[PDB]
Image (tube, rainbow, N blue to C red; front, side, top):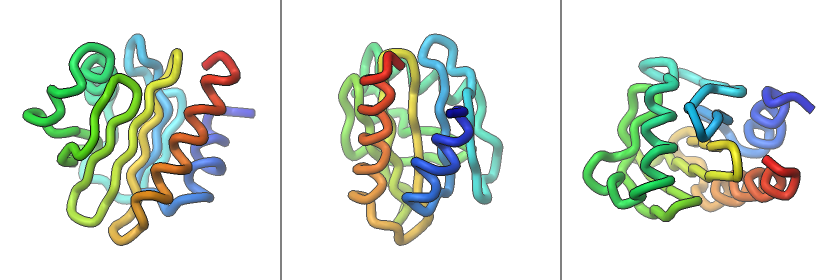
Length: 131
């Protein structure tokens, strides 16, 4: 039921997580998160920057990169509901639902398409439940 359970189970027991976070779109507040070994804890400021850009100008990520946990991911896909990035062999997938931002990045060497499938499936489930 809890937000932490979606992170720890639906995401992080189906992909091998470097980070996973569910946050509010309106303010970037964290609803739940998990991290392995990031240089910095993920901040509300980082999340709000991402949420604002996905809502208003997804192309901004091409110049600004995607910044989470003190790590810069390079953008490989961007629209107003789905953003993907890469930092070396770590993949990042971000979805916007009706009320939340779901972001996860996998450990080096984890298949990006597996990440994308799992994050998009949770995002669709949340949307279909009025989140």
